[PDB]
Image (cartoon, rainbow, N blue to C red; front, side):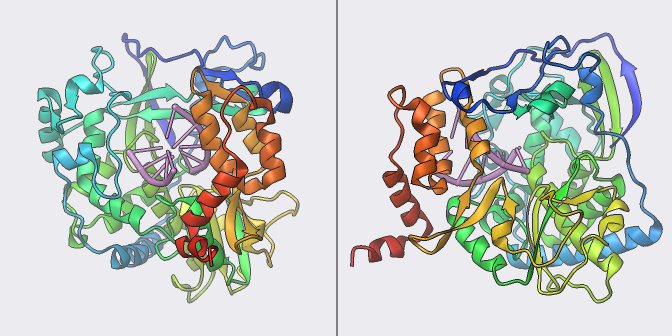
Length: 476
RNA sequence: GGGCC
RNA sequence: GGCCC
């Protein structure tokens, strides 16, 4: 986005500056080029001259203004994708009740009771539990009044900037490229879930190539579905964006919201309004208040879905800006936020599409840095999606999600205090697809200290998960 | 938020 | 609680 105003008010919004992450026994074995992100300006690991609060917002450098012709084309592409989207999902997009928005419906998880409430509740020392009853699904007097202001469309708010305590590559830790979470007020999150939660649940349930969304997928079971689909096409592209979320221009955001969330598709009129409030935002970091135009906040409800929808429209837009006669059936794609795999039987020049993505303020590069550009003839077994490769399991003939060993090693090298055992069981479900030799090697440092699931038990679990009949047929 | 285990 | 985004 674009930083348009910076103010210094005499009210501190104090941020966390101490990491919950600590090295594990595996850290001394794998020695990863990774570490916890810098949360303080006085972190000794930082380069001698890095100003963390400047590097945090450095992603906001532009809000690209699209021409009249480009805006018209974008609207056309947004309407065409929305047509496809709502044809598959249906038009049952009525507002969620206050109860259902908190408790969650089929395909939508419940709201977290003990997470950050946002502003101005954080300054008043209030939590989410004090403002909202998460057991009975009811709201207090404060949230009640705020919801009525949103209905009148007169509600205004500020985003609370939070440092993301996570493992990052050492080069980015040293540079101070700490990621940020834009924590929105809890009532804004609730009302967004009221406005588009039904839609959001449907997209999770109907995830796949047909809607171009993998949001709500289970890579264990869905890699077979995704893998066999993309295997049918002549060309497959692994496309990377740089600062996707930040580089969404106001024009693209506004037009998308206008075309996708129309009342004629079953939405409440305020669905479009509440999403449009994410375009021009105020951010609170300590004493400074930063006004940003364009870009997507990360703490907003349905950021993954919004980013995914934009990704789908971007591809159609760029192809239509370059080629004549492009439709939704010209290609196929799957997206999860900024992450994307594209495929076609046509030999599409993705290198030529670069300036067309630039007209949206987006920068595309091939994932693999072997070639000096995009090349044809790649298959599904060459690309990465959700940090996972597409590998064939020789035992079953099904596609399996394989994460790189260096990634798994980095994951296993750090943990939040008192969570190591629970973490190991989770990572074991990821590591099983690397094979018995690699699985054993990854969990060797933990042996005798924690319970590690056998490779066998997790393999048999996976076979039944992907195909129940195949597991039963093995007992022929 | 947003899912999946 | 963990992973991915």
